Structure formats: structure tokens, C-alpha cells
Image (tube, rainbow, N blue to C red):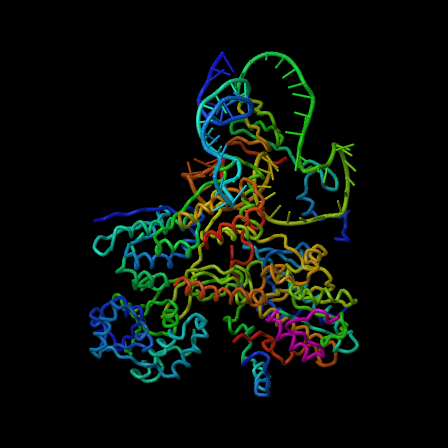
RNA sequence: GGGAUCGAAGAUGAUCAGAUACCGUCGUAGUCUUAACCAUAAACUAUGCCGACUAGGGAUCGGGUGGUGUUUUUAAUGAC
């Protein structure tokens, strides 16, 4: 393609290209062995809100 | 007050953590020392994600008040925000501006881009400064996504979040669209998750 | 011989004689663009002899293997670092694997000083690329039907966890485990391949952290296919220069400094780079490439403020 | 910023201010009970003592003065009074 | 049978050297046939001659002079002229040799040489075909013997205090005489 | 009293040449010190002294407090 030029054979493709979505979400914990890797201070935050999540803790030190 | 059904759910919490929205990075301004939970030993600060939820609903209740939806303008010059605002303006009735803002769009009628918004939503108050400044000449209120380093002039509602990560930008716009459609009748119930996946809002490089 | 169809990488081809390799394998293969490209007139003679013997065979992989490999390399994330030429070697090696063994069942389907002298010059130049000219650097360790000799850790990394066979071309033994360096962001803990200029990128591509990428020691196993970082247990964090005063674009002070002449195209009312996708950043990266090419043929920038921003400059 | 409670400052923020600039002034020194290793006789010592306080029973010395807090000798035991 | 020169790099120049190292040794080892190594034990570089494959005695001096110019702070493509050409020299002096001046007088003086945006220094390097570096109080001038003197006698008048406008006029005169 | 160097005055060399147009040699008082005088400077931040309030950040110099911190060493101290 070139700047300053457009035609149907682009427009039809662009509307197809940007409708793409993966089969499984990038945010799904399935990609991360089913856990969230977090620091100690992050797990303190969760406890303050209540809730209960499958966290995993790294010391960071 | 809003009933308990508006409380932050555990499922949404997982989304916010997975997208790293709670990483506030460094160079904290003196305003927005609230919204900070604690500092790590390495120096990154943890944003209180509980307050992020509260403010996001408040912003949604402001957008839902506008009498007709095309009067809402969503702006993103930065490229990681562009697909997000385009999708936001498709599910809601809002009007998008992506790329160059062209100065004199709220002042200077006799311009092809001339508009009269009722509300402006900005993705980055430092990069989008031209749009914020010009709004102040004409009595327009402003909502902004803000990181802990953001300047604060003329922003009325700050939503505190990680403003740099590609997933963080997309996720926040996604949640706003869900909340406005659900304060309106367009989604029938707050208890059932929305069918659109978050990934539809993410930036796509190659 | 120990192996059938030992593929030789460009580095093995230059640094050793064919009489060295003849003990190792019954047949030898190379991508034609590799053998065509190499230039050393001292090597060319030794190379020419071995080519006229016909024991060194030039073969191009099929397009299906290239695509099949390419998708895998994206899953590990190394596809951004591997060159087109490097992919051809991986595709060539393990499409002969399909010929010499039935099926694909052996492989994983998806993841989970010193004097410089005019004789030594060519080796030293390769060392300054970061490639291992010595062999066995950091090595810690259906039968032998194919093996790959290569000196580039980026190719080795892909080979190991796909359960390919790597040949220590300095010694003639297969490599099971190796240690090298990769980047790790200390904010989000994600791991990234080390770029070929050998220093960190300014921004983390995942979380957008600025300057948080640190080089980290890493080990890789064929057995597990996993990747393990090695952390210094007594690390002391340095926080100098994390916080500083910076101008605001909408202050009355800023609007006075902006002046009456509109946008000045010289000395362009400079704005600091703070985001990856800030349009100011796009200019500097491409302009850096241009200045590199211009200066090198004719002879033939920093971002952020650094640690000491808070100390006054006269 | 514009609205804040000046009459009920938080305990943490109060603890870090200079001793003259808290809402009401007050000292931050204190007194110690001290025993030498030999005798049973307890004695009371000011935490910023300027003199070299001896024991009462004998001329063994308990502390030495410095620019700030006093340095207690080795072998002594103490309790904050 | 063997002869060598060792030369030392001061610390502020150390990093530029590392970033350029792969550019400077190929010209020495190929064109001059010297052998070289960087000895990081003592922050020095060493040039060594092998009698069996070297052309003439001038090679060893050219190599050292090329490296010497680099540590003074000349650009790499300015130093490289010392391998190619044969009659280039370096001259150096410091402002306290001309006039004793101490505080803000000292700072103003070197500002007067550079000029705004460096434009005054740039002018001198054009009317005389020479390169100039200012390293705080010390000046180094690289060029041909007669060109060096023309440069010196005009940088001197700036530190004696003459206004820049008067000096630009003199540069015009010198340039026309070179035309003749 | 002392008197190396530099050097108002003074005695001398050249008077040619427009970038280098003011240059070379010798040298008295002075420049240093002891005991007495004088009371000026663009003696400048060209901003009188004392006291309260409106403002925030991290660099540096001196002092003090805290830390399950690093190193010197098996404590104290020192350095960070
Ligand atoms: Zn990161």
C-alpha cells in the first residue's frame, strides 16, 4: 500500500483484519499454570479487600 | 448508595491483576499519593485496585447521564490506545478521535473537524494535552485515565491505573463500555458476564 | 562417525578444517545461501576442496517445514531475534529428520588481554558478534539420525526445547544442557531473548516499565524443556534518580516559555520521552538506523535523564 | 490539601515530626534502670547523660557521654523505666 | 625483532573507545599489518610489530599517533586521517599561558571561543582547514603546519578579549590570501 | 631589613609591512618584611536589618535518631 491512497480492496480487508480475536484469552490463567505470580505487597492488598484468589508469592526481597 | 451488587467481584479482580493494572511504576506526583497502597523494596508502587473500581463506576454514571450519546468524545493520540477507542465508540454511540487532533477543533468553527462535545474522555493527559487545554476554553468537563506520574490540571475525574501496558489500556476501556451498557438497558443483568472478549480491544502489532 | 547428516552452521564451517569433521558424520549438509555468502579466502580453499569431494551437500528446506518451524519459534518468542537465514537452518535440519525417521513423534509438538593478529582477525570479529567460536561455552552436560552444530545461542535455545540434537562441534558430543544470558523484567517477571546488539531495550514490551529490564543468567534442559533463571540471593536495590521534578505542559509557566512564534521547528520546544508509543520515540529509532548506515559507508542519543538528574549542572 | 483535620493528626505522622513542632511539645528522652555485673545495686540513668556515671558501691563506670545518647558499658544490663 | 608502544586512555574517553573498538582495530591490523590488543588490566592499548610481515619503519609511529589523537578527543573520522595522510600535526596550549584569569572571567573566555551554538568555533575550522577541540581550559588544534598557526593567532585574540565581530572580518582576509 | 622574579619612570633597537600594527634589550621606585600613616574600588547579589505567612521534590555540606541492612572481624568503632 501507499499513503494517501485507498480503494475497496483495502477497505474490505481492513474491516476483516481488525475483527480478529484469539480462541483463548491472553488473560486466561490457563496460560500461566493456573496461578498469578505476585509480590508480598500485592497479596497484602488482596487480603485488605477480602476476596480469595489463587495467588502465588515471590519474595522479591 | 448503590446496592451491594455493585461491589468488586472476585472474577473481575483476576482480570485486573492479570493485566498488571496495579503496577504504578515510579516518579510519583505529590497529588495521587492517595490511591497508593504501598511501595515494594525495588521501588515500584502498588495502586489500590479497590479504589480503581469505585472511580470507574462513578465515571460510568456520568457518561450515562448525557442526553444523547454522540455528544461523548473519546480521544487517543498514542497508538496503543487507538483500537480501544474505536471499539468503545462502536458499542456505545460515542465519537472517536484517533491520531492527530488538529488544533482548533473545539474553538474555530469553520473547520472541517469542528465539534461541540458535551464530555471528553482522554487516555493520557500528558500526550493529549492539546485536547484538554482547548476544552478549558469552552466549559467542557474532562475524564482521564491517569498513572501516578500524570499531571493534574483541568482533569475532573481521574481513574488510577497502569497507563502504559498494552493490556492495561485495553482492559480499562473494555470495562467502561460494559458498565455504561449495563447502566442502560442494553445488557439485561449485572450477574451474567458479557459475551465480548477483552482481547477484541487489544493492540495488534504485526 | 557418530551421526547421520550433521548440519554445519556458518561458524563451524569457517573455524575448522573438513579433516577435523570427517571423523564425526557420514554426510554433511548446508543451506546454499550460507555456503555462498562466506568469504574468508583462507577458508574458501579448504571449503572448495571439501565441496569438490562431493561429501558436502547443499540442500534447501521445503516451505512447509519453514512455516511449521516459524509458528513454533513465535511461541517461544525467539522469532523476533532469529534472522531469515537462521530459520532456514532450523527448517533444513529438521525436515531431514522427517526423511530419516518415520513421522514426527520424536519432537515436541508445542512448547512445554589477548593479542589480535592478522591470522586471528576473522575469529576475533566473530567473537565481537557474541557467537561462541570456542564451542562448549557454558555447556553443563532415532539414535543420532540428525545433529546440528551451531555457535549461536538463539538457535541453540530453540533446538533444545523442541528436543532437537545439538552437536558440540569442537568435541563431537551431544549437548543436553547449557547456561547463557537472557533479559528479565523485575517488575512483571517476564523473560525475553537478549537482542543481538547485546544490551537491554528501554521499555518492557509487556508491562511498559521503563528501564526495568535486567540481564539474567538462564539454563535450559532438553530433558524438561523448561527455562530456569538464576538469582543472586543478596541483591541490593539501587533507587537513585527514580523521582524528580518535571515540567507540566499546561502550567502558566509552560505557556509563557512556549512563546509567540507558534511551533518552532528548530529546537522544537523539546518534550521528554516517557512512553514507548510516543511519536517522538518513533523518529529517534529510525533516525538512529539512518545515521548508522550513512556514517559507516562514508567512513568506508539517550532517553530518560539517568541516575544523577537531581544533581545540579553548572 | 484544601480540607484536612488539624486537630486529630495521625499517630504515624506525628511520630516523625521534630519535637518542637508537634501539636504540643514534649521530650523524647527517657530513664533507665541499670545494674553492673557485680553488685545487686540498681541505679537510674538518663538516656542522654553527659557525666560518666559511676556505680554507687564502687568506682566502676556505667556509661560514657557522646554527641547524643550515652553509650552504656559492656556487661551491664538495663530495663527501660 | 620486536618493538612496541603502550599508550594510556583517560577514564572519560574509556567508554567511547569500547563503543568504537570494532571499528578501529581492522584498519590497523589490515592496512598497517601491526598487531594490537586492549589491556584492560591497566586501561591501556598496546601496539606491537612483527618483523616478518611489515613494510617499513613508519608504520609503528602512524598507529600510535592515530590512537593518541583519539584520546585527546578528536572524532574517529578525524583521527583516521593520520593513517592516510603524512603531514598532519597536533598543537596544544592552555589559556593561562596567554593571560592569567580565574573565575567567571575564565568561564566567559571559553564561551567566547565556542560562540552561541558553537557557530564561532565552526567558523574558525572553515577559514582554516583544521579541527579544534576544547577540553575545559586546554585547546588542541589538528592540521597542517601553516594552517595551525593561522588558527592559533585568531583563537588567541578571542581570549585576550576582542569582540567576535572583529574576528570574523580577519577570517575573511586570510581566506582570500589562500585563494591568491 | 631584604632585594630571585616581574617591572610606572628612564636609557636604547626598528620604522618595514594592514591578521599577526604594537614589537626587542637593560632597568630605578615598587613587588616581600618590621614599626607608624592613609580610609578609597563596578568595596556588586548593582537588592538595609528583625519577625510571621503563602511550596513541593531530591542532590550536597555539618549534627542527631532508627534499621531483622552490606563490608572490615569472631564484638565496639570506621566506611557504605
Ligand atoms: Zn515488565
Spot occupied by residue D43 in the image (x, y as percentages of width and height)? 60, 28
Q: Residue at x 69, y 58 (%)?
A: C259
Q: Is residue E73 left or right of residue A7?
A: left
Spot occupied by residue C161 in the image (x, y as percentages of width and height)? 39, 72
| Occupied quadrant, residue F71 | top left
Vertical comparison of B16 with D38: above or below: below
Vertical comparison of B192 with A42: above or below: below
First to last magenta residue range: B78-106
Which of C255 and B4 lies nearest the eye of the viewer? C255
Q: Residue at x 26, y 76 (%)?
A: C28
Q: Is residue C169 left or right of residue B13?
A: left
User: Is residue E136 visible in this depiction of the protein?
Assistant: no
Q: Residue at x 29, y 56 (%)?
A: E32
Viewport quadrant of the N terminus of chain B: bottom right
Which of F39 and C138 lies nearest the eye of the viewer? F39
Spot occupied by residue C7 in the image (x, y as percentages of width and height)? 29, 75
User: Is residue A61 visible in this depiction of the protein?
Assistant: yes
Spot occupied by residue E92 in the image (x, y as percentages of width and height)? 43, 43
Does the magenta portion include C251?
no
Q: Residue at x 57, y 67 (%)?
A: C277
Q: Is residue E125 left or right of residue A10?
A: left
What is the count of numbered marks? 0
Does the magenta portion include B84?
yes
Which of C292 and A24 lies nearest the eye of the viewer? C292
Amino acid at each position: 500500500p501507499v499513503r494517501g491512497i485507498s480503494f475497496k480492496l483495502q477497505e474490505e480487508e481492513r474491516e476483516r483484519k481488525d475483527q480478529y480475536v484469539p480462541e483463548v484469552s491472553a488473560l486466561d490463567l490457563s496460560r500461566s499454570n493456573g496461578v498469578l505470580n505476585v509480590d508480598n505487597q500485592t497479596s497484602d492488598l488482596v487480603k485488605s479487600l477480602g476476596l480469595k484468589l489463587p495467588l502465588s508469592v515471590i519474595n522479591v526481597s | 448508595s448503590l446496592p451491594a451488587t455493585f461491589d468488586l467481584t472476585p472474577e473481575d479482580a483476576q482480570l485486573l491483576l492479570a493485566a498488571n493494572t496495579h503496577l504504578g511504576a515510579r516518579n510519583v506526583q505529590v497529588h495521587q499519593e492517595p490511591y497508593v497502597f504501598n511501595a515494594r523494596p525495588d521501588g515500584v508502587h502498588v495502586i489500590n485496585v479497590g479504589k480503581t473500581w469505585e472511580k470507574l463506576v462513578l465515571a460510568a454514571r456520568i457518561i450515562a447521564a448525557i442526553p444523547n450519546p454522540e455528544d461523548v468524545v473519546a480521544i487517543s493520540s498514542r497508538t496503543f490506545g487507538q483500537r480501544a477507542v474505536l471499539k468503545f465508540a462502536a458499542h456505545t454511540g460515542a465519537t472517536p478521535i484517533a491520531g492527530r487532533f488538529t488544533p482548533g477543533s473545539f474553538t474555530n468553527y469553520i473547520t472541517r473537524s469542528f465539534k461541540e462535545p458535551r464530555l471528553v474522555i482522554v487516555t493520557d493527559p500528558r500526550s493529549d494535552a492539546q485536547a484538554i487545554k482547548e476544552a478549558s476554553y469552552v466549559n467542557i468537563p474532562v475524564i482521564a485515565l491517569t498513572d501516578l506520574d500524570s499531571p493534574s490540571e483541568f482533569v475532573d475525574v481521574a481513574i488510577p491505573c497502569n497507563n502504559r501496558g498494552k493490556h492495561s489500556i485495553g482492559l480499562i476501556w473494555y470495562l467502561l463500555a460494559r458498565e455504561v451498557l449495563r447502566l442502560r438497558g442494553a445488557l439485561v443483568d449485572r450477574t451474567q458476564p458479557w459475551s465480548i472478549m477483552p482481547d477484541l480491544y487489544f493492540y495488534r502489532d504485526p | 562417525a557418530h551421526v547421520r547428516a550433521l548440519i554445519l552452521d556458518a561458524t563451524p564451517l569457517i573455524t575448522q578444517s573438513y579433516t577435523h569433521y570427517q571423523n564425526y558424520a557420514q554426510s554433511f549438509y548446508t543451506t546454499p545461501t550460507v555456503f555462498q555468502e562466506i568469504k574468508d579466502a583462507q577458508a574458501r580453499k579448504n571449503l572448495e576442496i571439501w565441496q569438490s569431494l562431493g561429501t558436502l551437500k547443499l540442500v534447501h528446506p521445503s516451505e512447509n517445514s519453514i512455516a511449521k518451524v516459524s509458528t513454533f519459534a513465535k511461541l517461544t518468542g525467539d522469532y523476533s531475534v532469529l534472522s531469515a537465514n537462521d530459520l532456514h537452518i532450523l527448517a533444513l535440519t529438521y525436515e531431514l529428520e522427517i526423511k530419516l525417521n518415520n513421522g514426527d513423534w520424536r519432537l515436541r509438538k508445542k512448547p512445554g588481554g589477548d593479542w589480535i593478529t592478522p591470522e586471528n582477525l576473522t575469529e576475533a570479529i566473530i567473537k565481537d558478534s557474541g557467537e561462541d567460536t570456542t564451542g562448549s561455552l557454558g555447556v553443563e552436560a532415532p539414535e543420532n539420525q540428525v545433529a546440528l552444530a551451531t555457535g549461536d545461542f538463539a538457535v541453540q535455545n530453540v533446538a533444545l526445547q523442541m528436543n532437537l540434537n545439538l552437536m558440540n562441534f569442537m568435541s563431537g558430543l551431544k549437548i543436553k544442557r547449557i547456561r547463557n544470558y537472557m533479559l528479565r523484567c523485575h517488575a512483571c517477571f517476564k523473560i525475553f531473548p537478549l537482542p543481538k546488539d547485546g544490551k537491554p531495550k528501554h521499555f518492557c514490551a509487556s508491562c511498559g516499565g521503563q528501564g526495568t529490564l535486567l540481564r539474567c543468567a538462564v539454563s535450559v534442559d532438553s530433558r524438561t524443556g523448561n527455562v530456569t533463571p538464576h538469582l543472586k540471593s543478596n541483591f541490593q536495590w539501587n533507587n537513585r534518580g527514580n523521582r524528580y521534578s518535571v515540567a507540566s505542559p499546561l502550567s502558566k509557566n509552560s505557556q509563557k516559555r512556549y512563546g509567540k512564534k507558534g511551533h518552532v521547528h528548530s529546537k522544537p520546544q523539546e518534550n521528554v520521552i516517557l512512553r514507548e508509543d510516543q511519536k517522538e520515540y518513533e523518529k529517534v529509532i529510525k533516525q538512529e538506523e539512518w545515521t548508522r548506515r550513512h556514517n559507516e559507508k562514508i567512513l568506508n542519543v539517550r532517553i530518560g535523564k539517568g541516575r544523577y538528574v537531581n544533581s545540579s549542572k553548572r | 490539601v484544601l480540607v484536612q483535620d488539624l486537630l486529630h493528626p495521625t499517630a504515624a505522622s506525628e511520630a516523625r515530626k521534630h519535637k518542637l513542632k508537634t501539636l504540643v511539645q514534649g521530650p523524647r528522652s527517657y530513664f533507665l534502670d541499670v545494674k553492673c555485673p557485680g553488685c545487686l545495686n540498681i541505679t537510674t540513668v538518663f538516656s542522654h547523660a553527659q557525666t560518666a556515671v559511676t556505680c554507687e558501691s564502687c568506682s566502676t563506670i556505667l556509661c560514657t557521654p557522646t554527641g547524643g545518647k550515652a553509650k552504656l558499658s559492656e556487661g551491664t544490663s538495663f530495663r527501660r523505666k | 625483532k620486536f618493538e612496541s608502544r603502550k599508550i594510556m586512555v583517560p577514564p572519560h574517553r574509556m567508554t567511547p573507545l569500547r563503543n568504537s573498538w570494532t571499528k578501529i582495530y581492522p584498519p590497523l591490523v589490515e592496512h598497517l599489518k601491526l598487531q594490537v590488543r586492549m589491556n584492560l588490566k591497566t586501561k591501556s592499548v598496546e601496539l606491537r610489530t612483527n618483523p616478518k610481515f611489515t613494510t617499513d619503519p613508519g608504520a609503528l609511529q602512524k598507529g600510535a599517533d592515530f590512537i593518541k589523537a583519539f584520546t585527546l578527543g578528536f572524532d574517529l573520522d578525524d583521527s583516521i586521517a593520520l593513517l592516510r595522510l603524512d603531514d598532519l600535526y597536533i598543537e596544544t596550549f592552555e589559556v593561562k599561558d596567554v593571560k592569567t584569569l580565574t573565575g567567571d572571567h575564565l568561564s566567559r573566555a571559553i564561551g567566547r571561543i565556542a560562540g552561541k551554538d558553537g557557530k564561532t568555533k565552526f567558523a574558525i575550522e572553515n577559514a582554516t582547514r583544521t579541527r579544534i577541540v576544547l577540553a575545559d581550559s586546554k585547546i588542541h588544534i589538528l592540521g597542517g603546519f601553516t594552517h595551525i598557526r593561522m588558527a592559533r593567532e585568531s583563537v588567541v585574540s578571542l581570549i585576550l578579549g576582542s569582540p567576535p565581530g572583529k574576528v570574523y572580518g580577519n577570517l575573511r582576509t586570510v581566506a582570500s590570501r589562500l585563494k591568491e
